[PDB]
Length: 55
Length: 56
Image (cartoon, each protein chain N blue to C red):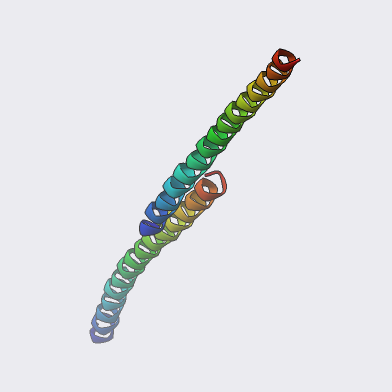
């Protein structure tokens, strides 16, 4: 009819916005966790270098 | 002669009446055509909404 189509369009705009936000948040999580794990690896290498210096 | 006049008058009235009835049935047939167009359009719009929603 008439109002039904507009209501469906609203329900679809919500769909697109929610899905896009979810995808963007997932990408953010991937990037942040990669950052953290690379920092942890750098910390490990520093520990090993400290061990060599102690030797 | 009198009977002929009477019969001719009744036949003329009958012709006029059938003309009126044929015009009336034409009008009502046209109205039914319009309503059939209405149902065709509303079913088409419902199908369009259905295909849009199923196809996003």
